[PDB]
Amino acid sequence: AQYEDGKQYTTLEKPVAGAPQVLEFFSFFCPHCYQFEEVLHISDNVKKKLPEGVKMTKYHVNFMGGDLGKDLTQAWAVAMALGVEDKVTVPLFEGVQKTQTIRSASDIRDVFINAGIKGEEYDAAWNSFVVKSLVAQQEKAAADVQLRGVPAMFVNGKYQLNPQGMDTSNMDVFVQQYADTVKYLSEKK
Image 1 (cartoon, rainbow, N blue to C red):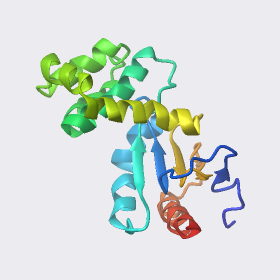
Image 2 (cartoon, one colour):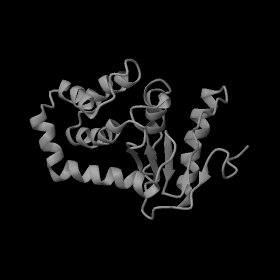
Image 3 (cartoon, rainbow, N blue to C red):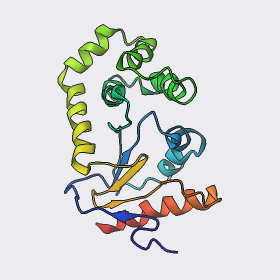
């Protein structure tokens, strides 16, 4: 098996010229969400070998049958705006992965304020242009690629992996094969 267009990565017919060599689509409501950036250390391990010829972007999805999820996308913007992710993500990742208390945009705000992001600070961050710029780019991120399966990854907006529960029984071959998928697709151009 050597990536047969569809096995370890398929191709979409709606590419995005300029797209990121590695667009990452993930929200705080997936089963791999918590296992993709915490236990499988696939986020750091892949970053340890990040070559300066591949832009790894990370975006939030807006399709988890959870209206607050859309606000959750505002979470990736309002957070990246105040670098409060590490702070609200912990109580946010464990909030949707062990409690289910995260089911209301108002809830996403409860954890946001838990990081000292008083509604005044966040309400201003969003009301601002830089945070709003990351918000319009977010909806535009999944709106341009469309996105239809979390977690989702798109290289240069042309090659998209297919991590839909591989279950290969080899977390070692998955971290190596994956690190390769991005290492070779980075050779596309």
